[PDB]
Length: 278
Length: 279
Image 1 (cartoon, one colour):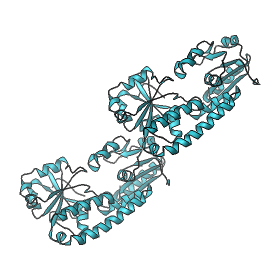
Image 2 (cartoon, rainbow over the protein chains, first blue to last red; image 1 turned 30 degrees about the horizontal axis):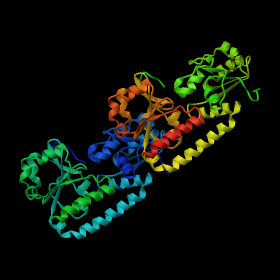
Image 3 (spheres, chains in turn red, purple; image 1 turned 180 degrees about the vertical axis):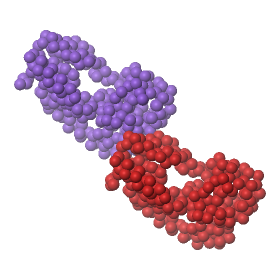
């Protein structure tokens, strides 16, 4: 297939590199510098707000050092993929000439995200909201798992998003696919070829790979609006012949990435509402 | 890149006010016998009418007319000196003392250095007690306002702007009204940041959206709340109308932005509190 898958006590001026943005928004902090905001990750309101902040890091993750220096931070925060720990050790000491820098490593695309993110929340002093959300998620998982054990046992789920010319099926080790799997949900054998990747990729001709799905989730932005490639997928002729489509069991899923525990809880709420309707 | 780059007599009777001296003699109710060329924008309309009757002894460019000073026959000459120009003014000071006792105070910056320098001149012309009362009242009012509107200060981003020819400026945390907002603990716009250690950051009209994070915008005016022509031209720009703060009706004039004395600095505080009340 064409796509290949997977320090100050009360700090005042925080630069948020990648994954730090979710942290400062949840803590009600206005950063003095951010990684370029992508709208799909945030509330419309949050995006309008984030767009007024200085940009210090790009999509491709390269850091504008002079811009960071210009912003005069008391604290620089960010998540780091663990496979790039070596590179960022050097990057780290550069940023230290400007300000105290706190990087946390995380592995993979599952619970590693919301845990790295919980650590950053501790560091900016929003540790307690953050730990409350962690405990609430663990509670809600247990509760939902038992309250709907029959539905969970009998229903095959799939989580999808579109890319250019192909769609993806999210694996059990990533994003909403992880959370579904944590609940004990059965998922389509379409996810299986992902192996250790986060998602498996298929052509439009292979849409009937999802035929064993009773319930289908498609990734959307915070307004339940699908990306243009996901919209293309839902407009495919073969999409209409899917049992889950004909049965009216196709649902938007906000915050599929579950970058924080708060996001992971919103995912659970949405899964619960679908479980209710079965 | 932008075009704009960033034995003193007891009870003296005949004072020549060079630069920064004018604010001192006015507040002390003294009629100086000579002044630096008065600049209308720094004074009330009525004050300027008075000052215009006095002999001019120093020009805008700060060159001193020694002859004019001797003709005024002062018994005391006073003024502020930018600390960078100290060497130059040792020579100047020596010349002036052939005429009369001469008192210069060095100051650094464009922040608290100013109002503290004019506080010293105030003491020297015998007005020390009114001056010191202003300094205390300013410190008091900063504490008061800081606590009373702590929530507004925490949530509101401010910006202080003025127009120049073809471009505009955003004032920095170390200068004029920007320094007073900073001293108060106000948060100000990212637009200051390119200034570094300079007093202001300059922008072209196309870059007006750099003020997009400001909730409240102040613009410098004269003592009659009249903006200068260059500031008017900023306020009439198309892109200005799209600013969140403009759309929110939170654009306000700001008098005595320069805050040359503690009394001026207090008038600035009074205008900021007034804005905070309307959140």
